Length: 228
Image (tube, one colour):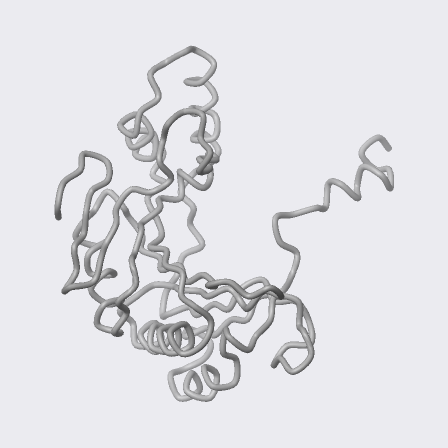
């Protein structure tokens, strides 16, 4: 009856985000609808809380598009979320090198290319384009956060499965650029966000792995400072 209490079960049900998600699934839904979908639910319009005048009268966690195939695999955070603990509680040397090996020691290989665009055409046209890619099969999944009351360049994260593979990372970078995105891209592996690697890190570990600037595309390795 313990955790079965109202107070306990209440805190036990809390999650990062409890709001629904605006999703276009290529699996269940072909590529003849995306068109109206993109026009029916733009990120500059779709609001985080479902504000009046929005295509959503209710909070929307994300705006997501899934292509043909998207195993919900996060690897095996279990052991990983244990190995990280065993290391810290040892004074062991924590470096981008040990975390890299960590993600490999648990087959949790997937990261995300992030970018933040100013609300409006840049975001809407970039996202639209990006979501026009997904449905075709060149990317696995991509999302874009809805506007937030006091504006602010919203988010657009692109996903690839296997960061250790710079080649697969670049093809995604390639797709993003082909969509005409001139913004800066920064790749962040799930291990980082998972094992909690904020920006005010006391362990001098950057939350970014790779970066990319328009030209063309200048892709860097912020780990050993090397140009791909």
